[PDB]
Image (spheres, coloured by chain):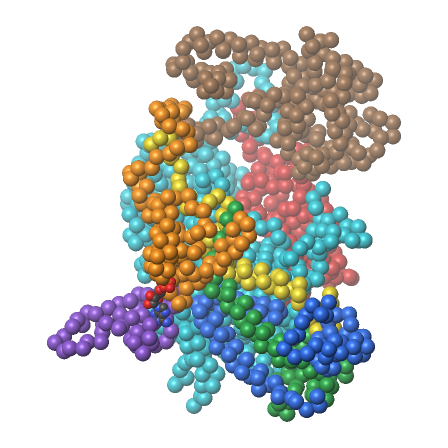
Chain colours: A blue, B orange, C green, D red, E yellow, F purple, G brown, H cyan
Amino acid sequence: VTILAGELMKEAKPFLEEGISSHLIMKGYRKAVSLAVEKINELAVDITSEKLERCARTAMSSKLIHNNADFFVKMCVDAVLSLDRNDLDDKLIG
Amino acid sequence: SLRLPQNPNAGLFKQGYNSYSNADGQIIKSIAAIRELHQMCLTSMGPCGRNKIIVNHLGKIIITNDAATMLRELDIVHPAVKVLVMATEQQKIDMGDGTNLVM
Amino acid sequence: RQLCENAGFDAIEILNKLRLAHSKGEKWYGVVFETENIGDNFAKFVWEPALVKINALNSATEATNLILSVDETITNK
Amino acid sequence: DIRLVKKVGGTIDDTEMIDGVVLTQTAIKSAGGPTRKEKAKIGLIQFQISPPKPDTENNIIVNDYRQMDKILKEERAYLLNICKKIKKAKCNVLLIQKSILRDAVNDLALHFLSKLNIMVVKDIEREEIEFLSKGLGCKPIADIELFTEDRLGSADLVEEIDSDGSKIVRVTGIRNNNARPTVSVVIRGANN
Amino acid sequence: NFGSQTPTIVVLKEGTDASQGKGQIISNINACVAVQEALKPTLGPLGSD
Amino acid sequence: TAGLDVNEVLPNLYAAHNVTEPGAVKTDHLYKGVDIDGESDEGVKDIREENI
Amino acid sequence: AKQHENRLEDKDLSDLEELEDDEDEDFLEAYKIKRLNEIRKLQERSKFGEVFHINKPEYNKEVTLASQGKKDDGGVYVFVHLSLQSKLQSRILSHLFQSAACKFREIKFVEIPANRAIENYPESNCPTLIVYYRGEVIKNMITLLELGGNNSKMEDFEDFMVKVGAVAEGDNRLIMNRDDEESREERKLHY
Amino acid sequence: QLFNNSRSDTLFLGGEKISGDDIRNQNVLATMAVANVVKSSLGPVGLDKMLVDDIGDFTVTNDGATILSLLDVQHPAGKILVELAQQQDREIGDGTTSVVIIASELLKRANELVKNKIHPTTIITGFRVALREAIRFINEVLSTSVDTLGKETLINIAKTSMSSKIIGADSDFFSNMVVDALLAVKTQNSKGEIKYPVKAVNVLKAHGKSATESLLVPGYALNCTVASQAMPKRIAGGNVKIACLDLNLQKARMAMGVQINIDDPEQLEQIRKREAGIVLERVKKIIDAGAQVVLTTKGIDDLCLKEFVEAKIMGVRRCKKEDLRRIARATGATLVSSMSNLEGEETFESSYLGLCDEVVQAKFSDDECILIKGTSKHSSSSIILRGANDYSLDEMERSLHDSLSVVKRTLESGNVVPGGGCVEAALNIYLDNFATTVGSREQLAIAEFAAALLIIPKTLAVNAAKDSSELVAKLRSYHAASQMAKPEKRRSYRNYGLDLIRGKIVDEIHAGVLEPTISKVKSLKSALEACVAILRIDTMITVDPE
Ligand SMILES: Nc1ncnc2c1ncn2[C@@H]1O[C@H](COP(=O)(O)OP(=O)(O)O)[C@@H](O)[C@H]1O
Ligand SMILES: Nc1ncnc2c1ncn2[C@@H]1O[C@H](COP(=O)(O)OP(=O)(O)O)[C@@H](O)[C@H]1O
Ligand SMILES: [Mg+2]
């Protein structure tokens, strides 16, 4: 989220040096982000088959336990399965 | 010749007190003092108006397009500009609409 | 862009391969670090939810539009 | 033998090997008689062109008003007969050393050389005498009696161009054809 | 009239930062690009800390 | 603030009010106003349909 | 305050006569008698005026006794020059001595070869300039790179004489203060 | 940018050490920091600036030549742009404001290419192939100098140099002035090569009526005062002789180190007389020659002034060396450093004297100027500028001095091209098709090089306080069709630019604005050579002073 917002502001730098007003640049992103949200809904899948394991391996990237994902993901998936639906208490994972 | 008498009978009042009459173009300066912060309001009226950063001495920041709100934090020296601050403050309290216009 | 620069690969050969290969790479076309090549991510079993993507663009669009509607800076004391 | 002359101005693409010996210093332009020379005989002067005096300090007295007429006439006569010997030897280009101790030239000596269409220069380094003599093929000169035509070189074109502010003296060709010639190339550039 | 100086009334307080011109919003972008440079190489699994 | 030249947009809007109320009833020149985004000239397509 | 002092301080005996018609006689002639007495003292002190080409036995007298002068502490500055004809700076400094000798007659200008001065002196350190005063060495100067080196001029040498206390700052003989007549002529016209 | 780096960690340097992309970013901000003052001064819509010396003195200046020279910058990367502004003033004399903006944007736009792991050696190679391709395209698109039956060119060339100045509105009056001035002071050299010496005309700082009523002098005007007030001020009649002397005419002492010594006191007065007589013998023969006007570099003593007042001769002291060469060159005289000849005798010949028709001394607002007009052998010219004060005339002096250099180049090289960012927009369409042909990594270098060239027409619209993208998009549309013109004139959609006073795209040939092509050539190479100097630096080593 941060390396992306900086690029939009860095890309808005030369347009501000030109005679483009401020509201014109904001109207472009606010109209384009509405299509990006709808496009991501089409990129995303409605997956229900095959019944957690793969999603945890990618979230552990860019830090220590990514290489030890073979051992930590096996027990990390069991952490949330103990929690039932609609409660999702974070203090229980203290 | 080397030095003036530096305004005699000035000990009637304190040294810190100063008078500002209509002459010497001072009413034009008060209009110019309004013109300093009035131009800040030009770019804040309308739907294409631009908000304003106001960093207080405590560090609490409020980003805004509304006059009555922005003028609360700024400490003002000119009394004629403070008339606009309290005039917009009256606009916000009673009706809560049309404060840039007051300014 | 930066995901491949940290890997030590040249960005021009990567970015030219992504654009011209979206027709057969309909949606699951992305970078692969293991084989030092570009291929389909569905076979590599790399997944990620969509909620990170929606909140990233909404937060990034809200962040850039906040100060883009600002042309002033006042600092008392 | 390969001198790299640095001149601020122009671009690097204009750099090219000059056929003759390029001089870094500019002309004096106190009189400004000649503009462009062709088929000039170059000579290297090591002594100083001045009114007659030894290297040490002297005292000249005047006991009569008629002596001043002889002094003012004979001082320029010592400059005149030097120009006559220069004209007899048909030496068209002269190179005078720095000579901080004794005055190199003056307005009187420049005036006689202005009529004969002879250029002059100053501020020559003592170490560059080997390069000018071996390059141009001109032996130096340190005495007026031993000045002759056999010790002088030759060249086809000796001129001083002003190429967009950068002033440079250039010599083209050497007819002596000595054993080991020399190389001279000017380096031009946008920045120093 | 009460003093020979007659000080000119400044609008804002002493020490307040500058105002409108050329480069105000560009400084905010460059300030964000500066903070963005520190978090730049930390992206992906082959990044740094 | 709309990124338009005020020297051309302002007097173009005065033409709607310099053609003052003729003998016909139900005159609709009162809803003419400025426009931030869009058509050239600027008198807005009424503030009507716009619902402002 | 300085406007009253500039009438007398900034005018010599030749320039003080300008104020004969304007200023009072008793105010002007009282100072002219003072400045006239100062001019007479410089004439009596003018014991020199050409370079004294000396030799060593004599050094023990010319250089040092002179430096004592009357010994009324009538001190006398004595500029020594350890000359070396092979060096280029030495011949330049010899010309400055004779030029300054014709102007400053009260200061003694001494010259001697450097090979004859000190046993086995370093030739690289020549030319050497020593300044004696009341028997004490005021300045043991090294080669003239400090004074421009090969490009040394008469103006630089006269400035050095003011630093060692040999010549006053506001002396009319110094080239820094001795403005040309054409310079003062333009000032009066544009005034 | 963020924080200061470690100071010599296990390196042992007395100064500072920095490396990586941080200093490369500092060079970009350094070139942009010095370029921001040059941005607002570009084009006719640009405004002037004033630099205060903290002593009350100030000077108004528009061109970035002397502005950056006065701004004492300590960062060495900015000094190259400072010297680039001074370099371009020497050779071309115009466009100092453009090379700083072009060189800064080439480094700014190339900064994105650095973090793409494109080496600078590959970037400059892509810039250089774009350069020589651009020079050949400039050599193709140039036009001839005839264009019609009449000249109709030199009046339009002056408007481009005169734009963006205080007297740009009066350029219609001054356009005839500059063309009439440089056509009068031409010369001959190198067996048929015509030259035009810049600064040979005299620019006088006069005060009075206005810049519109500035009278062009048909001849040279000497800026000096008369010696004595009892002399004749106006000298009429034809064939006025001009004498140009440089020898020392005031009474001087004997030789530089001699001493006058005499035993017989009888001849002590006689030697005093002949020293006073020997200087008057020179003045005696000038009166025998009959020189009405005499000019001297050195002073003139009162012993000589009495003879000029009696014989009605105009003696002027305090002339300068560079002026008298132009007086002798214009009036037909020769420079006389001393009076002598090959023979032993001493005399003066009448051939040394010049000729002119009229000489009149004029005074205007405490500025005495000797107006010499009607030179018979060769013509001359001078421009008497008039304005508010001296500091306003310094901008006019630089405005005229830059105008002579631009009109110099269009006569030395007849090839010209239109202004308004035409060639800057045309090279982008030419290089985009060439960028795809080369294939490999140099495509981005050639492409971003073309994108940096568009900053010249963009800055004209930004400073105009108008919408810039519409003008750039319309200028892009016409130039886009120029490459696809489909030759069979009907080759239209070329030689167009921006018109800022009206905000439309019209033909620059009919509008009357042009610029020589040689200014575009040297500006591009000097801008790229400066870009090569900054890109190749990796690490700085700043040593503190001892
Ligand atoms: N989309 C729009 N089109 C035309 N006019 C508008 C639009 N939005 C706002 N305006 C006008 O701009 C004016 C701004 O009023 P303002 O003083 O900012 O209201 P507030 O008191 O809420 O700040 C309004 O009176 C309105 O007529
Ligand atoms: N009347 C004009 N219309 C359009 N463009 C112009 C006009 N006058 C000048 N320009 C543009 O301005 C640029 C630089 O102008 P120049 O005269 O060099 O300014 P300065 O005198 O400040 O250096 C030129 O490239 C030219 O295209
Ligand atoms: Mg110009």
Q: Is residue D70 left or right of residue H223?
A: right
Q: Which quadrant of the rendered structure holds the N terminus of chain C?
A: bottom right
Q: Residue at x 55, y 34 (%)?
A: D73
Residue most extreme to the left: F23
Residue A3 visible in the displayed image: yes
Which residue occupies the foreground of this view, D127 or F42?
F42
Number of numbered discs: 0
In this rendering, the answer to whether H12 lies above or below H254 is below
Q: Residue at x 26, y 70 (%)?
A: F13
Residue H165 visible in the displayed image: no
Q: Position of residue B25 (x, y in %)?
A: 31, 41
Q: Is residue A85 left or right of residue B5?
A: right
Q: Residue at x 55, y 63 (%)?
A: E29
Q: Residue at x 29, y 67 (%)?
A: F10
In this rendering, the answer to whether H376 lies above or below H506 is above
Which residue occupies the foreground of this view, H333 or B88?
B88
Q: Position of residue F40 (x, y in %)?
A: 33, 75
Residue A67 occupies quadrant: bottom right
Q: Position of residue F14 (x, y in %)?
A: 24, 68
Q: Is residue H389 left or right of residue D70?
A: left
Residue most extreme to the right: G120
Q: Is residue A68 left or right of residue G104?
A: right
In this rendering, the answer to whether B83 lies above or below A20 is above
Q: Position of residue H96 (x, y in %)?
A: 50, 59
